[PDB]
Image 1 (cartoon, protein in one colour):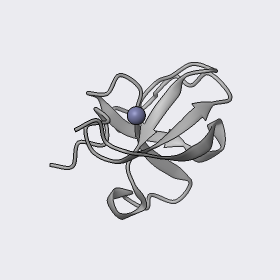
Image 2 (cartoon, protein in one colour):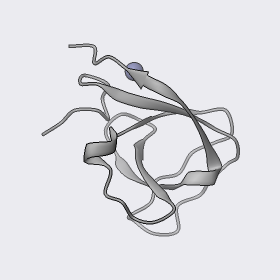
Image 3 (spheres, helix red, strand yellow):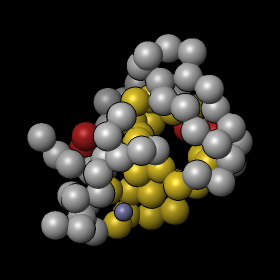
Image 4 (cartoon, protein in one colour):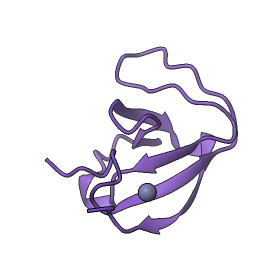
Length: 78
Ligand SMILES: [Zn+2]
């Protein structure tokens, strides 16, 4: 298990431009201003137009790519 969601392993961070309420259990919710952890390219599930992300560092899921701005790669805390 690659622990990008917790930030224990290397991860990408993104800032939410808008609020988002998950309609599917595959999706996760967040608010404008939230920082989200994203899986590295290799662990991205390549669902067209979505990114695998975590807000709370435990629940991972899909978020709409144009609701966030990718800021950069971050070293795991381990
Ligand atoms: Zn981090």
